[PDB]
Image (tube, coloured by chain):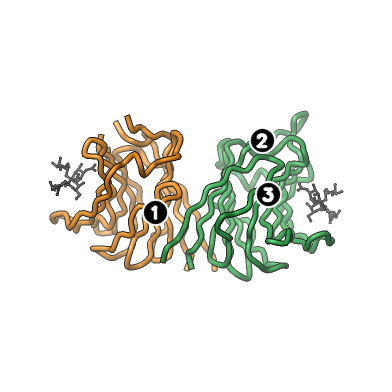
Chain colours: A orange, B green
Amino acid sequence: TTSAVNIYNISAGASVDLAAPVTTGDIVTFFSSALNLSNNTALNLLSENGAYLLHIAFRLQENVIVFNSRQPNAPWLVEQRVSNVANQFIGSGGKAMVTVFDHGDKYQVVINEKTVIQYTKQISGTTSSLSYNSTSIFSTVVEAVTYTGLA
Amino acid sequence: TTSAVNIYNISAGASVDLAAPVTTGDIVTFFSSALNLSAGAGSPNNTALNLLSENGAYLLHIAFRLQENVIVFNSRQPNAPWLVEQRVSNVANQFIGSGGKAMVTVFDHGDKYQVVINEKTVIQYTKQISGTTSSLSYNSTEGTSIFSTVVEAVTYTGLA
Ligand SMILES: CC(=O)N[C@@H]1[C@@H](O)[C@H](O[C@@H]2O[C@H](CO)[C@H](O)[C@H](O[C@H]3O[C@H](CO)[C@H](O)[C@H](O)[C@H]3NC(C)=O)[C@H]2O[C@@H]2O[C@@H](C)[C@@H](O)[C@@H](O)[C@@H]2O)[C@@H](CO)O[C@@H]1O
Ligand SMILES: CC(=O)N[C@@H]1[C@@H](O)[C@H](O[C@@H]2O[C@H](CO)[C@H](O)[C@H](O[C@H]3O[C@H](CO)[C@H](O)[C@H](O)[C@H]3NC(C)=O)[C@H]2O[C@@H]2O[C@@H](C)[C@@H](O)[C@@H](O)[C@@H]2O)[C@@H](CO)O[C@@H]1O
Protein backbone atom coordinates (compact mmCIF):
# COMPACT_ATOMS: atom_id res chain seq x y z
CA THR A 1 0.00 0.00 0.00
CA THR A 2 1.40 3.36 -1.03
CA SER A 3 -0.36 6.35 0.47
CA ALA A 4 0.24 10.02 -0.31
CA VAL A 5 0.43 13.38 1.46
CA ASN A 6 -0.34 16.59 -0.47
CA ILE A 7 -0.18 20.16 0.87
CA TYR A 8 -2.11 23.17 -0.54
CA ASN A 9 -2.26 26.88 0.35
CA ILE A 10 -5.77 28.28 -0.23
CA SER A 11 -6.42 32.05 -0.11
CA ALA A 12 -9.78 33.50 0.88
CA GLY A 13 -11.82 33.73 -2.31
CA ALA A 14 -9.81 31.04 -4.14
CA SER A 15 -9.95 27.40 -5.32
CA VAL A 16 -7.44 24.58 -5.86
CA ASP A 17 -7.60 21.47 -8.02
CA LEU A 18 -6.25 18.39 -6.18
CA ALA A 19 -3.30 16.40 -7.51
CA ALA A 20 -4.77 13.25 -5.88
CA PRO A 21 -8.56 12.98 -5.50
CA VAL A 22 -10.20 12.33 -2.13
CA THR A 23 -12.46 9.25 -2.09
CA THR A 24 -13.82 6.69 0.42
CA GLY A 25 -11.33 6.14 3.24
CA ASP A 26 -9.40 9.41 2.70
CA ILE A 27 -8.96 12.53 4.88
CA VAL A 28 -8.76 16.33 4.34
CA THR A 29 -7.61 18.66 7.17
CA PHE A 30 -7.79 22.48 6.97
CA PHE A 31 -5.44 24.49 9.25
CA SER A 32 -6.02 28.13 10.22
CA SER A 33 -3.38 30.24 11.93
CA ALA A 34 -6.06 32.61 13.31
CA LEU A 35 -9.50 32.40 14.90
CA ASN A 36 -11.57 35.61 14.69
CA LEU A 37 -14.75 35.10 16.70
CA SER A 38 -15.22 38.75 17.77
CA ASN A 39 -18.39 37.67 8.25
CA ASN A 40 -19.85 34.39 6.91
CA THR A 41 -17.07 32.01 5.89
CA ALA A 42 -17.22 28.70 4.01
CA LEU A 43 -15.02 25.68 3.20
CA ASN A 44 -16.07 23.47 0.26
CA LEU A 45 -15.40 20.01 -1.16
CA LEU A 46 -16.30 19.92 -4.90
CA SER A 47 -16.60 17.22 -7.56
CA GLU A 48 -15.06 17.40 -11.03
CA ASN A 49 -18.35 18.66 -12.54
CA GLY A 50 -18.63 21.49 -9.94
CA ALA A 51 -21.14 19.93 -7.55
CA TYR A 52 -20.77 21.01 -3.90
CA LEU A 53 -20.38 17.60 -2.24
CA LEU A 54 -19.95 19.29 1.19
CA HIS A 55 -20.38 23.04 1.90
CA ILE A 56 -19.49 24.05 5.51
CA ALA A 57 -20.66 27.61 6.30
CA PHE A 58 -19.69 29.32 9.58
CA ARG A 59 -22.20 32.12 10.35
CA LEU A 60 -21.26 34.17 13.40
CA GLN A 61 -24.20 36.62 13.50
CA GLU A 62 -26.77 33.83 12.94
CA ASN A 63 -24.66 31.72 15.42
CA VAL A 64 -24.84 28.45 13.42
CA ILE A 65 -22.69 26.15 11.27
CA VAL A 66 -24.62 25.10 8.15
CA PHE A 67 -23.84 21.89 6.19
CA ASN A 68 -25.33 21.33 2.71
CA SER A 69 -24.78 20.06 -0.87
CA ARG A 70 -25.87 21.15 -4.36
CA GLN A 71 -25.65 20.10 -7.99
CA PRO A 72 -24.09 22.56 -10.40
CA ASN A 73 -26.48 25.34 -11.52
CA ALA A 74 -29.25 23.95 -9.28
CA PRO A 75 -30.84 24.95 -5.94
CA TRP A 76 -29.32 24.03 -2.57
CA LEU A 77 -30.56 20.79 -0.93
CA VAL A 78 -31.63 20.18 2.71
CA GLU A 79 -29.58 22.07 5.34
CA GLN A 80 -28.21 20.44 8.51
CA ARG A 81 -27.43 22.95 11.26
CA VAL A 82 -25.30 22.92 14.41
CA SER A 83 -25.96 25.76 16.87
CA ASN A 84 -23.46 27.96 18.76
CA VAL A 85 -20.29 28.47 16.74
CA ALA A 86 -17.94 29.46 19.56
CA ASN A 87 -18.69 26.38 21.66
CA GLN A 88 -17.43 24.14 18.85
CA PHE A 89 -13.94 25.76 19.08
CA ILE A 90 -13.45 25.51 22.88
CA GLY A 91 -9.80 25.06 23.81
CA SER A 92 -8.60 26.35 20.42
CA GLY A 93 -6.33 29.18 21.50
CA GLY A 94 -6.05 31.40 18.45
CA LYS A 95 -5.72 28.60 15.84
CA ALA A 96 -7.99 25.90 14.48
CA MET A 97 -8.10 22.57 12.64
CA VAL A 98 -11.15 21.29 10.62
CA THR A 99 -10.97 17.61 9.51
CA VAL A 100 -13.29 15.84 7.05
CA PHE A 101 -13.26 12.03 6.85
CA ASP A 102 -14.88 10.49 3.74
CA HIS A 103 -16.65 7.36 5.06
CA GLY A 104 -18.45 6.48 1.82
CA ASP A 105 -22.08 7.14 2.69
CA LYS A 106 -21.26 9.88 5.25
CA TYR A 107 -18.77 12.68 5.88
CA GLN A 108 -17.56 12.95 9.50
CA VAL A 109 -16.56 16.55 10.40
CA VAL A 110 -14.24 17.15 13.37
CA ILE A 111 -13.29 20.59 14.73
CA ASN A 112 -9.98 20.20 16.66
CA GLU A 113 -10.72 16.94 18.61
CA LYS A 114 -14.58 17.23 18.65
CA THR A 115 -16.89 15.47 16.18
CA VAL A 116 -19.55 18.07 15.24
CA ILE A 117 -21.63 16.09 12.69
CA GLN A 118 -21.95 12.74 10.89
CA TYR A 119 -23.39 14.17 7.65
CA THR A 120 -25.30 11.69 5.47
CA LYS A 121 -24.29 12.45 1.88
CA GLN A 122 -26.94 14.02 -0.35
CA ILE A 123 -24.69 13.73 -3.44
CA SER A 124 -22.07 11.03 -3.81
CA GLY A 125 -18.76 11.19 -5.68
CA THR A 126 -15.05 11.91 -5.52
CA THR A 127 -13.65 15.24 -4.29
CA SER A 128 -11.42 16.83 -6.95
CA SER A 129 -11.19 20.46 -5.80
CA LEU A 130 -11.41 22.57 -2.59
CA SER A 131 -12.43 26.20 -2.13
CA TYR A 132 -12.55 28.83 0.62
CA ASN A 133 -15.08 31.71 0.52
CA SER A 134 -15.41 34.83 2.60
CA THR A 135 -13.09 39.55 6.77
CA SER A 136 -12.97 35.87 7.67
CA ILE A 137 -13.23 33.76 10.82
CA PHE A 138 -9.96 32.10 9.67
CA SER A 139 -6.56 33.35 8.50
CA THR A 140 -6.35 34.88 5.01
CA VAL A 141 -4.50 31.75 3.83
CA VAL A 142 -5.59 28.35 5.10
CA GLU A 143 -3.41 25.28 4.60
CA ALA A 144 -5.08 22.05 3.46
CA VAL A 145 -3.40 18.64 3.86
CA THR A 146 -4.86 15.54 2.16
CA TYR A 147 -4.08 11.93 3.09
CA THR A 148 -5.03 9.67 0.15
CA GLY A 149 -4.50 6.10 -0.97
CA LEU A 150 -5.43 4.82 2.48
CA ALA A 151 -7.71 1.87 1.67
CA THR B 1 -17.48 4.40 11.45
CA THR B 2 -16.39 6.92 14.09
CA SER B 3 -12.79 8.02 13.56
CA ALA B 4 -10.86 10.22 15.97
CA VAL B 5 -8.39 13.10 15.94
CA ASN B 6 -6.02 13.65 18.91
CA ILE B 7 -3.45 16.46 19.33
CA TYR B 8 -0.31 16.31 21.55
CA ASN B 9 2.47 18.78 22.36
CA ILE B 10 5.80 17.00 22.87
CA SER B 11 8.82 18.90 24.29
CA ALA B 12 12.38 17.85 23.47
CA GLY B 13 13.34 15.17 26.00
CA ALA B 14 9.76 14.22 26.87
CA SER B 15 7.18 11.58 26.01
CA VAL B 16 3.40 11.26 25.82
CA ASP B 17 1.04 8.32 26.41
CA LEU B 18 -1.63 8.23 23.66
CA ALA B 19 -5.34 8.43 24.46
CA ALA B 20 -6.15 6.29 21.40
CA PRO B 21 -3.53 3.75 20.27
CA VAL B 22 -2.17 3.73 16.70
CA THR B 23 -2.62 0.41 14.86
CA THR B 24 -2.93 -0.91 11.28
CA GLY B 25 -4.54 1.68 8.96
CA ASP B 26 -3.83 4.66 11.27
CA ILE B 27 -1.63 7.79 10.84
CA VAL B 28 0.72 9.92 13.00
CA THR B 29 2.01 13.31 11.76
CA PHE B 30 4.67 15.37 13.59
CA PHE B 31 4.84 19.14 12.94
CA SER B 32 7.96 21.27 13.56
CA SER B 33 7.94 25.06 13.44
CA ALA B 34 11.76 25.20 12.93
CA LEU B 35 14.36 23.38 10.87
CA ASN B 36 18.00 23.86 11.95
CA LEU B 37 20.35 22.56 9.24
CA SER B 38 23.38 24.65 10.32
CA ALA B 39 26.92 23.24 10.01
CA GLY B 40 29.20 24.94 12.56
CA ALA B 41 28.86 26.01 16.19
CA GLY B 42 25.21 25.58 17.20
CA SER B 43 24.76 22.63 14.82
CA PRO B 44 22.08 20.21 16.06
CA ASN B 45 22.82 17.06 17.97
CA ASN B 46 21.40 13.71 16.77
CA THR B 47 17.61 13.99 17.17
CA ALA B 48 15.00 11.19 17.15
CA LEU B 49 11.25 10.70 17.04
CA ASN B 50 9.97 7.38 18.45
CA LEU B 51 6.85 5.17 18.26
CA LEU B 52 6.77 2.88 21.33
CA SER B 53 4.68 -0.12 22.42
CA GLU B 54 3.06 -0.59 25.83
CA ASN B 55 6.14 -2.52 27.17
CA GLY B 56 8.61 0.11 25.97
CA ALA B 57 9.75 -1.55 22.73
CA TYR B 58 10.85 0.89 20.04
CA LEU B 59 8.54 -0.12 17.17
CA LEU B 60 9.99 2.68 14.99
CA HIS B 61 12.96 4.94 15.87
CA ILE B 62 13.67 7.73 13.37
CA ALA B 63 17.11 9.34 14.04
CA PHE B 64 18.18 12.47 12.13
CA ARG B 65 21.97 12.72 12.20
CA LEU B 66 23.19 15.90 10.53
CA GLN B 67 26.97 15.45 11.02
CA GLU B 68 26.96 11.82 9.85
CA ASN B 69 24.53 13.03 7.11
CA VAL B 70 22.03 10.14 7.42
CA ILE B 71 18.51 9.36 8.65
CA VAL B 72 18.56 6.03 10.55
CA PHE B 73 15.40 3.85 10.92
CA ASN B 74 15.44 0.96 13.43
CA SER B 75 13.57 -1.00 16.13
CA ARG B 76 14.44 -2.71 19.37
CA GLN B 77 13.04 -4.71 22.23
CA PRO B 78 13.26 -3.29 25.76
CA ASN B 79 16.80 -3.36 27.17
CA ALA B 80 18.06 -5.38 24.17
CA PRO B 81 20.45 -4.58 21.28
CA TRP B 82 19.23 -2.47 18.37
CA LEU B 83 18.13 -4.49 15.30
CA VAL B 84 19.22 -4.02 11.65
CA GLU B 85 19.49 -0.35 10.60
CA GLN B 86 17.96 1.03 7.41
CA ARG B 87 19.64 4.25 6.27
CA VAL B 88 18.78 7.11 3.94
CA SER B 89 21.68 9.41 2.99
CA ASN B 90 21.73 13.22 2.70
CA VAL B 91 19.49 14.79 5.33
CA ALA B 92 19.06 18.24 3.77
CA ASN B 93 17.93 16.79 0.44
CA GLN B 94 14.95 15.12 2.15
CA PHE B 95 13.61 18.53 3.26
CA ILE B 96 13.89 20.56 0.03
CA GLY B 97 11.02 23.03 -0.29
CA SER B 98 10.49 23.09 3.50
CA GLY B 99 11.19 26.75 4.18
CA GLY B 100 11.97 26.63 7.91
CA LYS B 101 9.23 24.17 8.95
CA ALA B 102 8.65 20.46 8.45
CA MET B 103 6.02 17.71 8.60
CA VAL B 104 6.92 13.99 9.23
CA THR B 105 4.09 11.49 8.59
CA VAL B 106 4.08 7.78 9.54
CA PHE B 107 1.46 5.45 8.03
CA ASP B 108 1.03 2.06 9.76
CA HIS B 109 0.32 -0.34 6.87
CA GLY B 110 0.44 -3.53 9.00
CA ASP B 111 3.56 -5.18 7.56
CA LYS B 112 5.38 -1.86 6.91
CA TYR B 113 5.62 1.72 8.15
CA GLN B 114 5.63 4.27 5.29
CA VAL B 115 7.49 7.47 6.29
CA VAL B 116 6.85 10.73 4.37
CA ILE B 117 8.78 13.98 4.89
CA ASN B 118 6.50 16.85 3.67
CA GLU B 119 5.21 15.27 0.39
CA LYS B 120 8.15 12.88 -0.29
CA THR B 121 8.11 9.18 0.68
CA VAL B 122 11.57 8.52 2.10
CA ILE B 123 11.22 4.81 3.09
CA GLN B 124 8.86 1.82 3.13
CA TYR B 125 10.22 0.23 6.33
CA THR B 126 9.55 -3.50 6.77
CA LYS B 127 8.63 -3.99 10.43
CA GLN B 128 11.13 -5.80 12.62
CA ILE B 129 8.77 -5.80 15.66
CA SER B 130 5.01 -5.75 15.34
CA GLY B 131 2.46 -4.28 17.69
CA THR B 132 0.33 -1.29 18.61
CA THR B 133 1.83 2.18 19.25
CA SER B 134 0.81 3.44 22.73
CA SER B 135 3.32 6.30 23.38
CA LEU B 136 5.52 8.76 21.42
CA SER B 137 8.82 10.35 22.47
CA TYR B 138 11.26 13.00 21.25
CA ASN B 139 15.04 12.79 22.09
CA SER B 140 17.69 15.43 21.23
CA THR B 141 20.59 13.92 23.21
CA GLU B 142 19.96 16.67 25.86
CA GLY B 143 21.35 19.22 23.42
CA THR B 144 20.39 21.30 20.37
CA SER B 145 17.55 19.84 18.28
CA ILE B 146 17.06 19.84 14.50
CA PHE B 147 13.36 20.65 15.16
CA SER B 148 11.52 23.21 17.31
CA THR B 149 11.74 22.72 21.08
CA VAL B 150 8.03 21.71 21.06
CA VAL B 151 6.79 19.42 18.25
CA GLU B 152 3.04 18.94 17.73
CA ALA B 153 1.79 15.42 16.96
CA VAL B 154 -1.61 14.69 15.43
CA THR B 155 -3.01 11.16 15.27
CA TYR B 156 -5.85 9.91 13.03
CA THR B 157 -7.26 6.65 14.44
CA GLY B 158 -10.25 4.38 13.99
CA LEU B 159 -9.84 4.57 10.21
CA ALA B 160 -10.04 0.89 9.17
C1 LIG C 1 -33.48 29.15 7.72
C2 LIG C 1 -33.08 28.89 6.26
O1 LIG C 1 -33.55 27.95 5.65
N1 LIG C 1 -32.21 29.76 5.66
C3 LIG C 1 -31.81 29.53 4.28
C4 LIG C 1 -30.43 30.16 4.03
O2 LIG C 1 -29.55 29.42 4.97
C5 LIG C 1 -30.04 30.02 2.57
O3 LIG C 1 -28.79 30.62 2.49
C6 LIG C 1 -27.90 29.95 1.67
O4 LIG C 1 -27.50 28.76 2.33
C7 LIG C 1 -26.61 27.96 1.52
C8 LIG C 1 -26.41 26.62 2.26
O5 LIG C 1 -27.68 25.98 2.39
C9 LIG C 1 -25.31 28.72 1.28
O6 LIG C 1 -24.56 28.90 2.55
C10 LIG C 1 -25.60 30.11 0.68
O7 LIG C 1 -24.45 30.95 0.58
C11 LIG C 1 -23.42 30.42 -0.29
O8 LIG C 1 -23.86 30.20 -1.65
C12 LIG C 1 -24.31 31.40 -2.34
C13 LIG C 1 -24.81 30.88 -3.70
O9 LIG C 1 -26.13 30.31 -3.52
C14 LIG C 1 -23.12 32.38 -2.39
O10 LIG C 1 -22.06 31.84 -3.21
C15 LIG C 1 -22.63 32.73 -0.98
O11 LIG C 1 -21.48 33.60 -1.07
C16 LIG C 1 -22.23 31.42 -0.25
N2 LIG C 1 -21.87 31.74 1.14
C17 LIG C 1 -20.61 31.57 1.62
C18 LIG C 1 -20.31 31.96 3.03
O12 LIG C 1 -19.77 31.03 0.92
C19 LIG C 1 -26.67 30.85 1.48
O13 LIG C 1 -27.09 32.04 0.67
C20 LIG C 1 -26.38 33.25 1.05
O14 LIG C 1 -26.48 33.61 2.39
C21 LIG C 1 -27.75 33.80 2.98
C22 LIG C 1 -27.38 34.04 4.43
C23 LIG C 1 -28.47 34.93 2.24
O15 LIG C 1 -27.73 36.14 2.52
C24 LIG C 1 -28.42 34.68 0.74
O16 LIG C 1 -28.84 35.89 0.13
C25 LIG C 1 -27.01 34.42 0.23
O17 LIG C 1 -27.00 34.08 -1.10
C26 LIG C 1 -31.12 30.53 1.52
C27 LIG C 1 -30.90 29.76 0.21
O18 LIG C 1 -30.37 30.71 -0.65
O19 LIG C 1 -32.34 29.88 1.90
C28 LIG C 1 -32.83 30.10 3.23
O20 LIG C 1 -32.98 31.43 3.51
C1 LIG D 1 27.62 2.25 10.95
C2 LIG D 1 26.85 1.66 12.12
O1 LIG D 1 26.39 0.51 12.07
N1 LIG D 1 26.67 2.49 13.21
C3 LIG D 1 25.93 1.98 14.39
C4 LIG D 1 25.35 3.14 15.22
O2 LIG D 1 24.35 3.73 14.32
C5 LIG D 1 24.62 2.67 16.47
O3 LIG D 1 24.23 3.82 17.15
C6 LIG D 1 22.94 3.70 17.74
O4 LIG D 1 21.98 3.59 16.68
C7 LIG D 1 20.64 3.41 17.26
C8 LIG D 1 19.72 3.12 16.07
O5 LIG D 1 20.22 1.96 15.33
C9 LIG D 1 20.22 4.60 18.07
O6 LIG D 1 20.07 5.80 17.18
C10 LIG D 1 21.26 4.86 19.22
O7 LIG D 1 21.00 6.09 19.92
C11 LIG D 1 19.76 6.08 20.64
O8 LIG D 1 19.70 5.00 21.59
C12 LIG D 1 20.71 5.11 22.63
C13 LIG D 1 20.57 3.88 23.54
O9 LIG D 1 20.99 2.74 22.79
C14 LIG D 1 20.55 6.38 23.42
O10 LIG D 1 19.26 6.41 24.09
C15 LIG D 1 20.69 7.59 22.48
O11 LIG D 1 20.42 8.80 23.17
C16 LIG D 1 19.65 7.45 21.34
N2 LIG D 1 19.81 8.57 20.39
C17 LIG D 1 18.80 9.36 19.97
C18 LIG D 1 19.15 10.53 19.10
O12 LIG D 1 17.66 9.12 20.30
C19 LIG D 1 22.66 4.95 18.62
O13 LIG D 1 23.66 4.98 19.73
C20 LIG D 1 24.04 6.31 20.13
O14 LIG D 1 24.60 7.03 19.11
C21 LIG D 1 25.75 6.47 18.45
C22 LIG D 1 26.06 7.48 17.32
C23 LIG D 1 26.87 6.28 19.48
O15 LIG D 1 27.24 7.58 20.03
C24 LIG D 1 26.34 5.42 20.58
O16 LIG D 1 27.35 5.39 21.60
C25 LIG D 1 25.10 6.08 21.22
O17 LIG D 1 24.49 5.29 22.23
C26 LIG D 1 25.64 1.84 17.33
C27 LIG D 1 24.97 1.12 18.52
O18 LIG D 1 23.80 0.36 18.13
O19 LIG D 1 26.14 0.77 16.48
C28 LIG D 1 26.87 1.16 15.33
O20 LIG D 1 27.92 1.98 15.69
What type is the residue that disc 2 sits on? Asn
Q: Are marks 1 and 3 in contact (CB under 8 Å)?
A: no
Please tell me if label 3 and label 2 are on a single chain: yes
Between marks 3 and 2 in the image, the one whose residue lies nearer the viewer: 3
Relative to A84, does residue A150 appear above or below in the rendering?
A: below
Residue B3 location, x and y as percent?
A: 45, 61
Earlier sequence position, callout 3 versus callout 2:
2
- Label 1 and label 2: CA atoms lie apart by 36 Å
Residue B24 location, x and y as percent?
A: 57, 67
Please tell me if label 1 and label 3 are on a single chain: no
Which element is circle 1 on? strand
> Is A34 on the left-hand or right-hand side of B21?
left
Q: Which residue is nearer to you in this view: A142 or A2?
A: A142
Q: Specify whether tag 3 is near ligand 2 (CB below 8 Å).
A: no
Q: Specify whether tag 2 is near ligand 2 (CB below 8 Å).
A: no
Residue B50 location, x and y as percent?
A: 68, 53
Q: Which residue is nearer to you in this view: B17 or A137?
A: B17
Residue name at image x 51 percent, y 51 percent: B6
Residue name at image x 31 percent, y 46 percent: A43
Which chain is indicated by disc 3?
Answer: B
Q: Residues within 10 Å of mark 3 (few under 14, many from 20)?
A: some
Report which residue position mark 3 lands on. Answer: B137
What type is the residue that disc 1 sits on? Thr
Report which residue position mark 1 lands on. Answer: A115
Which chain is indicated by disc 1?
Answer: A
The quadrant of the rendering that contains the N terminus of chain B is bottom left
Q: Which residue is nearer to you in this view: B87 or A122?
A: A122
User: Residue B36's mark?
Assistant: 2
Which element is circle 2 on? loop
